[PDB]
Amino acid sequence: LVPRGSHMYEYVNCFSSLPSDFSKADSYNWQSSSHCNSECSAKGASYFALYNHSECYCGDTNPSGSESTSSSCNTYCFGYSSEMCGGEDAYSVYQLD
Ligand SMILES: [Cl-]
Ligand SMILES: [Cl-]
Image 1: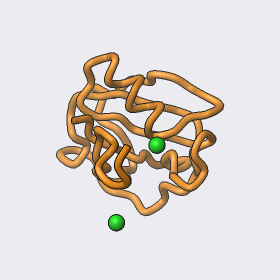
Image 2: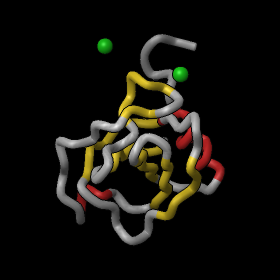
Image 3: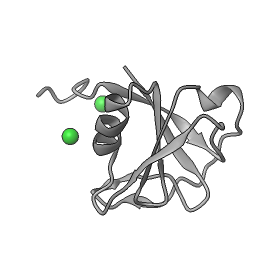
């Protein structure tokens, strides 16, 4: 739509783990940040997290307050390979608008 600001979500950080309020929304062969945003927006969630190429989690608390950051969000999103869907042991966390 526009080249910058078209996505109704903002990257927070890469985290080692998720707070207990995060729950798996889906596993998907075409997982991506925009797919997970739509999944979690439909649930009314405030945050979403990508994990290990294919998994999408939704949650309501900011992991910044409770989990350590990570530099190992290195598993590409199956549905958008230039973006990382967390890592094997790390979560790419975004905030929904
Ligand atoms: Cl830019
Ligand atoms: Cl897009």
